[PDB]
Length: 369
Ligand SMILES: OCCN(CCO)CCO
Ligand SMILES: [Cl-]
Ligand SMILES: [Cl-]
Ligand SMILES: [K+]
Ligand SMILES: [Mg+2]
Ligand code: NA
Ligand code: NA
Image (cartoon, rainbow, N blue to C red):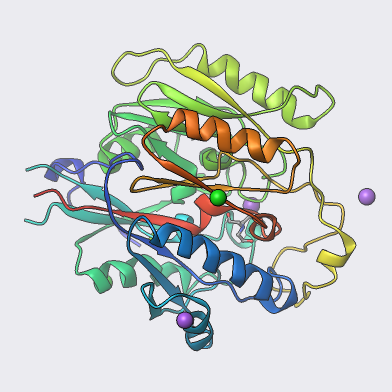
């Protein structure tokens, strides 16, 4: 669609860091049988666990399709709000609004990016995203929060900010011809400065190995822990295709400076021992000719970097790895000493459909007064 006549930055807005205070978290509800095994029941139960864990820290709203509303309302505790919303799949980091705030009429707004199911008619993950195109408008209308609209295609999982002017992104995703092939790097930067209130960029060339379907979203590779400090997906195994990506990202990060002129300190957050979809898993997924196939043997895009920050809580995946799960809890607990770190077992169930906890959440900042 078209772009708002004035940008967020013209009105004083910017995207705050994820660790700033939230009013609530938004989460979708999975259902489609060609992405979620066994009629989505195992994933529904893990989404409900993620939502419940977040609800201990802050309010949660789960949005569920007309067909699923009663099921979601049964599976969620009563203090989680459940609302009806049509969607083509349940990845609200990507299809939901990117909220923005200001200091100095409302002091919160949301950005409704364009969307094409991570690469459109050619290269997208499913063939119909027309419900997804309305999710951001519907969420913002629910909350009576003003909306800015962009014509640019963007997913929230592809951008990360420190709240101090820096934006961390991947070239693999935002420069892919399947997103905005009419725009240069410089033009994409200009739009992100105007809409996120950022001044400078850190461009990692590639995202996580195994995340070809999003084209290497930043949120599954590297994120800020606080200004000047990032967590980076890591392996020491030179035989894993991940290694060359991690080493290249570390080299870029060690030659980067943030928008306020700090060097970037990197904390390595080790990926689990490689995970692969099993035949039993793949056999529970339909092939209706509407979505990409989910095949036995696929390397899962599993990284503990795909955690979510809530008010006083870190909600982190657990993948069953007998050392990396506990290492991730420890590293995150040390890196966020004022937060409680909660692990979600069976996060694998989300990773079978190509993302994890961070991909299924969208924070609504508290509105500054
Ligand atoms: O399958 C649609 C959603 N999926 C895309 C990558 O497989 C994970 C969310 O980014
Ligand atoms: Cl609207
Ligand atoms: Cl826990
Ligand atoms: K894709
Ligand atoms: Mg949108
Ligand atoms: Na219930
Ligand atoms: Na195999």
